[PDB]
Image (tube, helix red, strand yellow):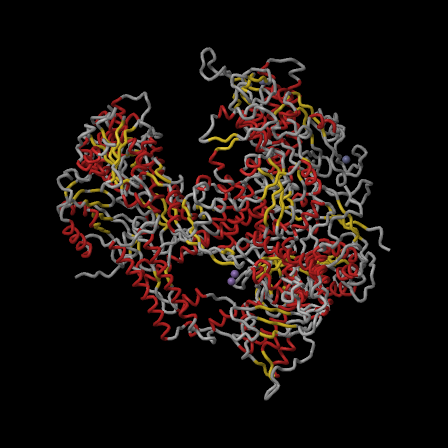
Amino acid sequence: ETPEGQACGLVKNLSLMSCISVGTDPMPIITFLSEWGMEPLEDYVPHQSPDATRVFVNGVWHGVHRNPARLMETLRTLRRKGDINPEVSMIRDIREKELKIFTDAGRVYRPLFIVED
Amino acid sequence: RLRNLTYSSGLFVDVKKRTYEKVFIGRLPIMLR
Amino acid sequence: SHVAEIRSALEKGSRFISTLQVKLYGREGSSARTIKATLPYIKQDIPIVIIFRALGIIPDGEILEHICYDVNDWQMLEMLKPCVEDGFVIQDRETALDFIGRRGTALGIKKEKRIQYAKDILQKEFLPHITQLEGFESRKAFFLGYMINRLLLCALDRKDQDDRDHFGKKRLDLAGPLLAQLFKTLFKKLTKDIFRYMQRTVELAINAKTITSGLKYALATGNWG
Amino acid sequence: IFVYQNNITPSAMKLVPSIPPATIETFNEAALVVNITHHELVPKHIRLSSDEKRELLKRYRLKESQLPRIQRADPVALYLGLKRGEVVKIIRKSETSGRYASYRICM
Amino acid sequence: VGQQYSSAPLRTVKEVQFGLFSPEEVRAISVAKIRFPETMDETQTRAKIGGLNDPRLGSIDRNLKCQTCQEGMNECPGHFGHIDLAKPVFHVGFIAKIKKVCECVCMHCGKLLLDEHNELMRQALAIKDSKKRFAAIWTLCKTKMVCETDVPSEDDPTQLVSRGGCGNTQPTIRKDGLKLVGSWKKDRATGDADEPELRVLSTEEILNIFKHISVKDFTSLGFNEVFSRPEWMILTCLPVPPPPVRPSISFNESQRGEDDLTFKLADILKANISLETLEHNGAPHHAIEEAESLLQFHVATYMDNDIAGQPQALQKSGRPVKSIRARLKGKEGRIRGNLMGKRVDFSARTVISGDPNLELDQVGVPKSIAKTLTYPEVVTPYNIDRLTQLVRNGPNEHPGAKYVIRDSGDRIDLRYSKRAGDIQLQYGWKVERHIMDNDPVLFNRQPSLHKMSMMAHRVKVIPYSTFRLNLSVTSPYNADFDGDEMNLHVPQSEETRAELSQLCAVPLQIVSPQSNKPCMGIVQDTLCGIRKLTLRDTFIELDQVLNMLYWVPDWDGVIPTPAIIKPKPLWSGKQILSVAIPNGIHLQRFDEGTTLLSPKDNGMLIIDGQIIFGVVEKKTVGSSNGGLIHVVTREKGPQVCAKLFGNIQKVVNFWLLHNGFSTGIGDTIADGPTMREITETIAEAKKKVLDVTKEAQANLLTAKHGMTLRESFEDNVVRFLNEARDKAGRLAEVNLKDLNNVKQMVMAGSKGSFINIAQMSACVGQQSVEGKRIAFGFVDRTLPHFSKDDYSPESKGFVENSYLRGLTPQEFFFHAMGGREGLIDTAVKTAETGYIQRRLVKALEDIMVHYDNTTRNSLGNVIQFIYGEDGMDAAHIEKQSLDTIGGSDAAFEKRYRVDLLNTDHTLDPSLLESGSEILGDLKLQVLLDEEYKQLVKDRKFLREVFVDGEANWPLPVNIRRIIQNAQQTFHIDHTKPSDLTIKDIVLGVKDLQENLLVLRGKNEIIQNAQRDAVTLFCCLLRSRLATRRVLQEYRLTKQAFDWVLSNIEAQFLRSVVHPGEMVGVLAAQSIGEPATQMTLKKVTSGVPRLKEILNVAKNMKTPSLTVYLEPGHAADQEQAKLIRSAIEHTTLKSVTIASEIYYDPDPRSTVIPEDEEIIQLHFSLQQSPWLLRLELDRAAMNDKDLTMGQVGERIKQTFKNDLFVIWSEDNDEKLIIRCRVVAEEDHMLKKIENTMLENITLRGVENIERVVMMKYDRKVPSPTGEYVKEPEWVLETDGVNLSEVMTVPGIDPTRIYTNSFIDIMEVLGIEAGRAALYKEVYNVIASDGSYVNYRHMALLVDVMTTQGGLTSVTRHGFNRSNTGALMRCSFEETVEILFEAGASAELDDCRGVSENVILGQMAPIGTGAFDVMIDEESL
Amino acid sequence: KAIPKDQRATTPYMTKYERARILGTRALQISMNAPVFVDLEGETDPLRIAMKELAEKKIPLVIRRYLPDGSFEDWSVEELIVDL
Ligand SMILES: [Mn+2]
Ligand SMILES: [Mn+2]
Ligand SMILES: [Zn+2]
Ligand SMILES: [Zn+2]
């Protein structure tokens, strides 16, 4: 569903199940992150920890975390409870040493069935 | 819709007047439902 | 040959989209390819080294550690070689802060004020979405390093340049945020109009309609920016 | 015709139009390594006598400006040593009629 | 008009000469002097004052008195006033130009600062474009600020040559609204010469400097000695427009009235007077200056309202304003508003619907629309009753009329008129009737890119709304019936009627110029139906024959005697269709396996209007070249053909209606097994792809030369997956039965191609965006449903399924991706094509074929010395076989050799009557030898032209047909000997050629031109009417033969282009229309290319050379390589593995092991300790056929001695160049290292980056004569350098081609430029299979080339491209366009359509390209 | 500028545009009851009569063909071969 010609591909339509994130406070997460072993960036030394996965949150580099998957689990599990807002988006880029969390409104998202082992 | 009106609402702020050196404040068209 | 754009803006307060570009000068094989960032209000592209110094990260070794999280990555560090040189003239935070101050200021202005101008720019304009308060200079240095990083990691044919058309990195602005843009820009005139009821009062004078008309106006047309 | 290898001093260039009406034409060796007129797309250019020229512009009743044009510096013109005002009959193989003959006046 | 008489000849403006009013003329023509800035009330005595609104100028007060020119407010053409300006003044329009001229001439002697002595100036001066010259001169002269005294001559710089002996410095002149300010200097910053002196260059200074510019100097600027002198740009003397330009709204009597120009002039006059009343009274300087700049302001504002403000104080304290620029803002924009087609009158628009029951040239007009549009018909004894009947019928009954217009031009409004039913129509009144059945109306569908989309039809009033079109008139209009509206326009005058129905009438448009074929065919149902009706298995019971028969109105009532009379009287499907066909129609065509028994009921033979064999489908009955419509049109007339569409449709449609044709999902299902073959075919490619994957993941795929692994892996995969879809698609097309409704449409020709069946039934095939498989949008994977780095077809976007089978979500989304690509640039192709077509027209708009068969533009320039090189009209050309060109020399002799002196190669006494007495006739065999040597030159000539060997070339007069008509018109029997003499043929044809006349001039040049224009048609003719041919094959008797000759001559003349032909527009819309169908190996093709080409873009997207190897070595794959390498730009960068700067201080021993052996080796039969060491890669090192020595002594000859070079030799396992500078060293080296890796040219021509070899199959004559394909290696290059590549040893420098027609021009000249440009434009038009008759592109390519250079089409000028100052008034500033036209003496030819509309005249185009006059001769 | 009856280089044949325009001009006359030259063997419609006049070589008009240089040839509709 795009209108032909001039607006073509520029005017788009939400697939039935897209909603748009409403925008959530990242305070409690950033709070949880350093509670969960995120190293503060102030206290960060790379030649010392280059295996460090860097946690971003709404774009802000908040620091670092060795052993992210154990952060990632929790982050996922929290959101899957309700304790972190469902709309909150967390992407770990394993091969980039990055874990970017997103809480800002405007992110178009859709629902999926969780397949977990 | 019929009356060509605006489905707004009274935006009432709450002011603290203090000498230093309810209150109606605008209308917000309410989005239906 | 490359550019590393952030478009940092505060989620709340007053949305200031103050773009920071981190530009790699020269194309592959132009003699001494230097990196410079482009700070807002600062009418000249500052060698990135000098920013780190103005950010309190003085010694090369330290600066490079903020950029190049890998001591063996001799290729990247070798890319920066001319940066370290490009910021050679400047060796302490104040000279650095001054260097910037001067590219943001007229020739008349006094060193302290100059430094102070560069101190406020780095604190409020440079990467404002990190922190706008004080103690967070390492927080920016690090982010700025990471920018220079990614920029070079792209320059070293080690990274694909960002897909402009990836949707995850788009946002859809809706009823909520739109009515908040105007409502910010209209409450700011209501906060301004009420200010012309103090400077102007020597001895209930509130335009309801500035906002009623303003929202109502925008929504009756499609007039936002 | 002065043929030369790499180039000439633009000073020695300003030495060319100097011995009138005698024309000095200058060909960089490289421009001559191949005869362009032997090229496929290059048709027979035939410098017309001012007498054939008179006939042309008459038979057809054309002011010189109404003829198709060729540049003084056009590689075929230069090769022919075309002097401005000189017309060339261009006999070209046509796919419509066998030959078609068009004229260009040196500009 | 103005029923009075004037003895003065009645004429039409043929030319408009634009110029500037010299102050001299401004007085000379003027009637007043105009002093008083007021009007009326002369001490109260009303009327006018000798100052304004009267002194001699136009009258008011209903008074006829007006310099004795009488007449009054409606008949007088207001006479012009005069007003002396106290001081010179810049005319606003030219302030720009004035300044600009002032920068070119010296400001003291009036001497062009740059002469014929300066070399960059003779190129500036030689330019013929008065506008472009002036610009080129100015950009050259504004540098100058010193009017040089002595100039370096054409000799020694020692030797100065004198010129204008005035040495003074010029100011740099800047503008300030109305004042030009000049600032001097005795050089820029030199001692005792600093600080400029700003002084305002006054009008009085400039005017006098302008006067000092020579007739020679200012003519080398735009200016005209006679029409526009620079001085005249400066007003001294102001024209005063009279009362018709500036009215006076006197509300009956006793009230003020004078227009807003009158007041604006009144204030000029005021300032003028107060400027005089300060010189006459004497005054200070900044008082007269102030009084000057007030005047200058008011003259300025008078013409242009866009300066330092707006003086709006004219009788109103509220302040509005009107100038003469801002008068044209309602008169350049009210003329342009009516120049853009807004007030659309006598036209009507509605949905179109198809209607198989209208004739081909009808348009069903709904009654209600018919009742709305009128035709003014003059009451005439021939029509008095009908008209009277209408007038009674009235505005509401159909065959009625809206208005009866009597002598006096009164309009009785039959609708609201107390005499509606009581009007005695008198002769000579106009009744404005409704359009009724058979009125020619012009029916057009926008966007109308195509003479064929504005055609004239006969009206046929019909019931319901919507226009109704005959289906076959459908594609000429590119119209369908899914909502298209069309405009109908009623020609209003009788000649305007005549023109429509005589030129644009739909029948006259069947064979169209655009592709020398019919452009209207039988279509959709009628096509599908006709094929069916035509099959052998189609037979018609008597009961239904009679209807079908009766349906054809042109039926003669004879029931054809059935082709089966046995058990059941039973007609062929062919037989009855054959009654739609008129007599005298023959058609032979042969397909792949047609015989005269055509098994497959293949091919086509129709004889005397009975299709003898062949299924009738698109080929025959469609719009195709040879087809039955082409034939019937040429053979029997356009109208009789047009009627044929009717018959055929009616018959076939009637037939189809009772037969029935459908299409279901069943038609789109494959044979159970075919589906397994298809599924197998696909799954057979997914291995291929998979194998190449494994192959490449292993790293075993070798990159094809100048193509990356990843680049060439995809390339393979894509082809596999296509070979698949395609072999898959064929697998279903072969299956589908001859019942298959889908295939049943496909056989017949109506909508439906292979790709369609292919995608519906077999594989949908590979999707693709930007000509690649679907790209990894997510990181290294196309959807979040695949794993990372999945390069399989399924992942990267092969739609495996048919549409019948349905698409998987991925397939669905990838299809959606490809789809969106399609629509996105279907919107691009529409938008760019839309505008190209509008540029292409504007470019060629004015080219017309004049009476001399020359083809010229508006100026009169010869573009083509004969239209499309042969003087033929493209709608009268057919593809024809030049037989002389083809087959073995052996064969050539067999057909054409008649040798009487040879019992073997003589004409056998059976062919010929006098056949025996011919044997051994020396004298004859000298004629027949003439014939044959001539046929031989011919074959030779032809092989020189069509190097290709292409036998079949669009030529006029179908000679094959004429002969086929002779053989039928005379019932020639191929049994008895012909009564021809050899002398009859041989001389007859020789005599015929002397009669084919495109050109008629009695002189030699024309007779030579004529001989050429006819050359090609003559070889066809000679090869067709060869003596053996005429007798052996044709068997023509003297009668039929004499007929064939006179027919060939008849048609040939009929084939000659008519003077009048807007051949250019034709040519532009012949190139445009098809481009408005281009909706789509790696070179830019189609509209980007077309917009690239027409644009003459020097910065092409895909610059390529195509070089051919020298004749003797074409096959040598190794020499193709050896050239490739010696051409492909090969840098050090491409051959070096790594560079390293070592500190290696001892130039003997070395801290590098692998180099100890190499310094030793360079000591057998200054230097820095810093070493630049390059490690080179053999792979690319020997690949580019390169030596260490060669790489080495290259660098060593690049860096003179400034570098000490040494290199490992070609045996050593590691290849190494070690280099030292010969201390700031480590930095000079990283520079040199770069100057090496980037700059140094090891091998090749610069700019040639990739160089691919390819085998090209080439058509070349073998020794025995016939055309044999000879494969050749052909290098194709990414990058163009045609000059340096042309010269490379071992290429065929004769054939080397680039698509950059620009470099071709620059290297090979303009004529070759044009040749190439035509090959490019044509490649664009050929790439979409489309055809456009050569002459159209020729004319485009000629127009681009006429002026010595490649002049772009896609606008070059901001004003023009070939447009008179009057024509479609462009910019909101036509004033500006006109101002320049004044200054440059623009000479308008009035060959425009607009200029002449502006003038109330018809264009000298086509029907207006000659004059009609009343003959005093006719007895 | 005029070119003598001999030395006419222009087609002896009437051009489709000329016919279009004679027929036009001629019909425009026939339509305003100006007198017809042929026998109206039935016809009521102007153009059809104009065509009949052309057909029977009875149109009394001269066509003035202008050459691009300005000179012109005159032909009499009578002279002009109508073969289109
Ligand atoms: Mn359609
Ligand atoms: Mn449509
Ligand atoms: Zn008058
Ligand atoms: Zn001078």
Question: In the figure, is residue D12 to the left or right of E382?
Answer: left
Q: Which one is nearer the viewer's eye here, E457 or D39? A: D39
Quadrant in which residue C34 is drawn? top left
- Position of the C terminus of chain E by quadrant: bottom right
- Above or below E589: residue D84: above
The residue at 81%/41% (across/down) is: E6
Residue E434 in sight in this render: no
The residue at the far bottom in this view is E567
Quadrant in which residue E242 is drawn? top right
Q: Position of residue E359 (x, y in %)?
A: 64, 67
- Above or below E615: residue E1202: above
Q: Which one is nearer the viewer's eye here, E1140 or E176? A: E1140
Q: Which one is nearer the viewer's eye here, C80 or A49? A: C80
The residue at the far top in this view is E192
Residue C177 in sight in this render: yes
Q: Quadrant of ligand 3?
A: top right
Q: Count the numbered circles shown.
A: 0
- Position of the N terminus of chain E by quadrant: top right
Q: Position of residue E68 (x, y in %)?
A: 81, 34
Q: Position of residue E715 (x, y in %)?
A: 35, 55
Q: Position of residue C6 (x, y in %)?
A: 29, 40
